[PDB]
Amino acid sequence: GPLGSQLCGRVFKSGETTYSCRDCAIDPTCVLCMDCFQDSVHKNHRYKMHTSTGGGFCDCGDTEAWKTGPFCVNHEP
Ligand SMILES: [Zn+2]
Ligand SMILES: [Zn+2]
Ligand SMILES: [Zn+2]
Image 1 (tube, protein in one colour):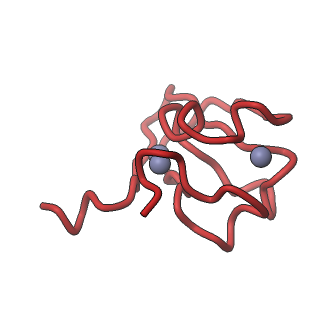
Image 2 (cartoon, helix red, strand yellow):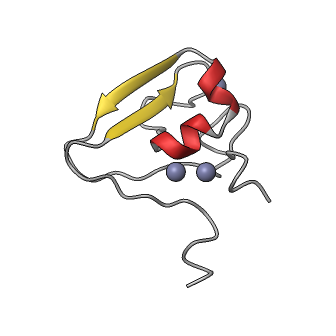
């Protein structure tokens, strides 16, 4: 419902591509799904793509994961 979809929360499946902003990630485990990455400032930053082995989740919206621009435009309040 609306509460479960207010933030991204995408859970990755094996074979999907994750994105991390190397400039803004607090640590290497901070990741974004493709849509949030492409809808965020980090599309313009130094980034790393990493194919998921399944599991993990998108960190769009977590101030404690990103030094700047924690929300993509879609999820930004
Ligand atoms: Zn996302
Ligand atoms: Zn997002
Ligand atoms: Zn960034």
